[PDB]
Image (spheres, rainbow, N blue to C red):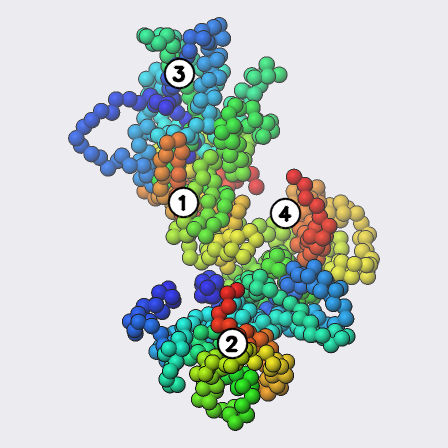
Amino acid sequence: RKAAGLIQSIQRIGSNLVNRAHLITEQLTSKTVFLNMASFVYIVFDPDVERNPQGEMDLLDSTRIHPEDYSLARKMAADALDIEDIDDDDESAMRNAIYEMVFPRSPPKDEDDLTFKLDELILDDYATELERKHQLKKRSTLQIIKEELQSRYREI
Amino acid sequence: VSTSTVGARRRRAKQQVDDEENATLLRLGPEFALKQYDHDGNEHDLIALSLSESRLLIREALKARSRARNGGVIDDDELAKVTSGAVANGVVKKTLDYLNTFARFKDEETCTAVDQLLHNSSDCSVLHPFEIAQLSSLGCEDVDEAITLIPSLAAKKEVNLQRILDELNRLEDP
Amino acid sequence: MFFLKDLSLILTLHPSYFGPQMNQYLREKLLTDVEGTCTGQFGYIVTVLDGMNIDVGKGRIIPGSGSAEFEVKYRAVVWKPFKGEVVDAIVSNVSPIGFFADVGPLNVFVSTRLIPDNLVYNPSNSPPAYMSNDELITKGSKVRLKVVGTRTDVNEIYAIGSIKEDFLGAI
Amino acid sequence: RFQAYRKSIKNYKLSDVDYSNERDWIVEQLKLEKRDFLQHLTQAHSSVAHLEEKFEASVKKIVDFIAIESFEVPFIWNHRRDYALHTYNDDSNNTIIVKLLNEDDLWRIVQLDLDYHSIHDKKAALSSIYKQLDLDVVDPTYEEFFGSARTLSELQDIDDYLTFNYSSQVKNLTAVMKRKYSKYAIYDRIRQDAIYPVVQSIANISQMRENLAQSKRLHQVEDPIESPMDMIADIMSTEKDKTTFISSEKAYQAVKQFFSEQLSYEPFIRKTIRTAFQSFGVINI
């Protein structure tokens, strides 16, 4: 019943869904249902439409990363880029950092993509910092995020 | 398969409302009518059987057959095993279990006294045999309860229902 | 309800059995073919009275087939439920759609729509049952039910009971 | 899926005390079921202290998630599996993952929480019945077996014990009319009859319960100065007006059956027999 109503609402609204946040903004569902189903439903990102930075279609929407951890994924991406100019609250800079990391305008000179540099980050340190700051056991979540950045929806 | 002694019943045009089976209305159909005929064609009354009478008759017939099959030389399981046919054995087992687990009167003399009371009574001289069987079977305790369970007795208010019920309860072995 | 009825049966005998023991053989054949059977017109035949002294008469030879046809008349005990009758029962199974009880050879199914609402079905109970605050009806429990409808089959009878009225339910 | 599971559950939001009791019962049920897994984990990973304590904490957290936050199993397994696994370091400080639970265990959690939500209504009904009894002295057996009551079979045993030993009180509370015959009417008559003092004199109920619970002799069953037949006949002769029995043998049989019923309705005997059968019983066909 819920899937039928959801697909009917999506069809009435338009041909496709723009981003995961619209499942809440467009009154398409409630809160707990969205939180449960958030990471298991995705929209295929396309670098052709990526040209505008204002693109509502988030790249993280094509990953297993939960929407509640999009900020954490952005922070990890900023950590891998080693760019200390961006602080922890400049979300537009984080979005541009992900844009560069996954779909750089200039292809890397070597064969190691910017997503590969995430392997140099120490997940244990970040997990300990998160557990100290907000009491969250998310080391497995950080591992999953790194895996998703290394390959979007690898077959399980 | 088996055919009743009542035959004919050819086509007509009238349709009657006393054709449908209904225990409350005491409409038992043609084959269970109040008047029956034996093999000689003489008048015969419908023969109802209470669980006590039915149990007595089935036990007597089964033990007679068991004695005859052994050359004229008690357990319900053995008695059921006497009969032939697996489905027949199961059916007689189920009937015996029902009768045993709901036998109000397991003694011949108690059943005889109950039948005498329910037949020779002046009030019971009009009672339908189905009503008599229901009264002796259900083991009702109250006039209101009996009337609710047996709607036919509601229209028969010339019956000493309460004292007859108390007599049955007395005759019932505690 | 149990009754005494005078029934008749048509019995056909093959010529290979035309011996001195013809009568007794006809008797056992009748007993095997009548005891325990279920006819919609009459109900269930449980026993045949005087099973060893039944008159069989003279058999008639069927022209063109040799076999003899016998007309056997006998008295038997017959049980048949009636619409609107209240009888005792024993519950045989409990299910969410309803519970199945047994009234002698007849198995009666009672749906939830004919059960009082307070007797909510409890599947967690061991064994699962339809229970209320003061009532609990499970497998093997005595129940007093009223037969509402009877369904006629080829050689079977299906009855429907109810416990929704007074003086019904658990006993 | 949760709505379908909870469709039959009329009352779902338990109290905090009931919530903690549900968590404890779920933990105990898992410990009983996964005893082999816990034993193997403890034996292999003997170096780590209180692995099972962390297991209990993780089970409590999972129950909290499922009940309060209404999280489906795959979401928990894909985004909360950090709670389900305990990362300990060995003597070499190598990070070792310990898979405390699997998805099948989460399904078991859902089934167990449904089961406890079902039995919670029954335990509340028994509590309400006991409160309606309003005993002048709180029955020690009632408290002792209600505190340790985990299965609905034990709740049924409690109900049977309470109804048997307070048949008159329970019947009055029902009265506080369909002529259903009380199966305990004969025992109530025995209680009202003059032979009930003899039944007392056979053995003290409180002393019997204390001796059985202790499993050793705390008091000696004092034998009355006169034989059972002597006392029965004497009371029958001196109380012909009230003794409803006809013969002394009939009163003797009634006393024996009443004592048998008293022994049968004792929760401790039933519990011991059930434990013995569940532990060392065999199956024959």
Q: Secondary structure at mark 2?
A: helix
Q: Position of residue B140 (x, y in %)?
A: 45, 43
In front of the other: label 3 or label 2?
Answer: 2
Q: Residue furthest top?
A: C20
Q: Secondary structure at mark 1?
A: strand
D32 sits left or right of C68 in the view: right
In the rendered view, would you say B73 is above or below C44? above
Q: Position of residue D103 (x, y in %)?
A: 57, 64
Q: Residue furthest left?
A: B13
Task: Tell which circle, 3 or 1, labels the residue nearer the N-terminal end.
Answer: 3
Tell me the amino acid under the disc marked 3: Leu
Q: CA distance from mark 4 to mark 3?
A: 62 Å
In front of the other: label 4 or label 2?
Answer: 2
In front of the other: label 3 or label 1?
Answer: 3
Q: Quarter of the image holding residue B153?
A: top left
Question: Label 2, on which residue?
Answer: A149
* Circles 3 and 2 in contact, beta carbons < 8 Å: no
Q: Position of residue C147 (x, y in %)?
A: 39, 42
